[PDB]
Length: 235
Length: 235
Ligand SMILES: Nc1ccn([C@@H]2S[C@H](CO)[C@@H](O)[C@H]2O)c(=O)n1
Ligand SMILES: Nc1ccn([C@@H]2S[C@H](CO)[C@@H](O)[C@H]2O)c(=O)n1
Image 1 (cartoon, rainbow over the protein chains, first blue to last red):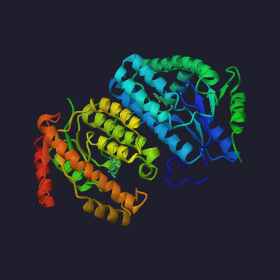
Image 2: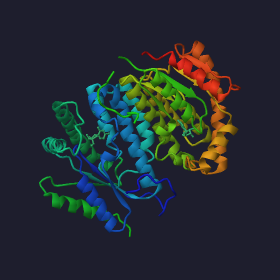
Image 3: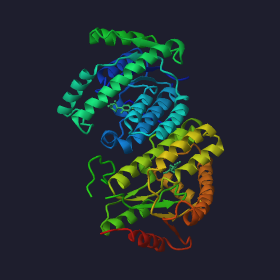
Image 4: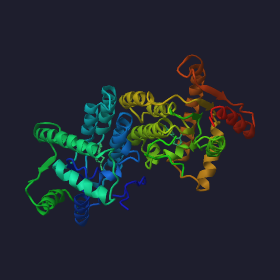
């Protein structure tokens, strides 16, 4: 439907535009992603919204129920599938991608599993060497939107989704779900501090970093993001 | 149908049995794989035959039409998807797997792309470090069957399959198809010499290496492989 896996020739030169949300969106931001992509299509871009549920491996549950065995290959899978989707749609085909998560944020999830002992130091070093080669072939996002919901909100949304059958219970216990969500939130607070430095005198000079007002209603929030993304659409 | 992606608990201890074909099966060996798996099910094993067409990424054609960009991530994908399939079905769930290709043979296909310049030396080093960590978690196959068809036969089978629509044209030209098939055949002749040494005083002590009589009819060939695989089935 979104033609994400078309190996035919480009039907346009250069890469498209790359917009990414960054935060602990453990319950997803699918309405925001899809609405934003739709607003870019209205402006005339070939725009696709890509939630993480496009990248979840069929074995996803095992990264949380059998972490010592599956967290390393499943983390490799997130990185790799995201890489290939961007390399084809954004770079090769010049499309506009609105991502729930950029290629810059996957390493944080490896760091979590390393601190728990599910991924070894040697596995992490191998991941880092492949990640460095892959990320060197993908442009930085053009617009990064920092949105880290608080863990209690993430968990309330997840609990409702699991109860209503709209997503499977992917964790092995209620406590494990809460603990991963809190660990990711804590890491994302540090990651976002890093982003504010990166954007000013690190490798994200050249990227627009957008921070929201957490007290702003949702409606002021999509409107703010939409305005900045529409600056990129070339008719 | 084959329940390859079941994240539920094991329904059996220890890993299952691991049988692999090794050779330039560019047109596939799907009848042999499926027949052999069926013979092991008859003997009472939970056996699955896995052809490479289970692992072909949706972007497969780009590794041959845009090799300089896609050969590295697509090779990572072959390794990773094969790893996860084995880690779940063979190791975690103790099933018996009859593979068209084992995890030991993927590195040869990276070597091909390195010699053509499609994969850089630095990309290959990163691949090798991840491959070493992944392969350390997968048992050696128990029975390896050397079958390297000659390139003219591979190409005759491929040409017929493409003409009849039973598989897409995955190469960008007739000449590129012939050249990859010949490069793989040549590498496999060297790989099979290596196997004969590995099995006797390298890391495949402990594995049964089966070599066929290339002059033997197909029927003597499935019968020979079936006899040796059935030595492994525990009722
Ligand atoms: N590299 C990654 C990216 C995402 N996730 C999980 S997958 C699930 C998305 O629906 C949600 O739990 C994310 O936090 C992950 O574990 N590792
Ligand atoms: N690591 C690998 C494994 C397999 N193949 C190709 S994929 C196709 C199978 O139908 C056939 O062409 C194989 O030779 C590959 O390129 N790299």
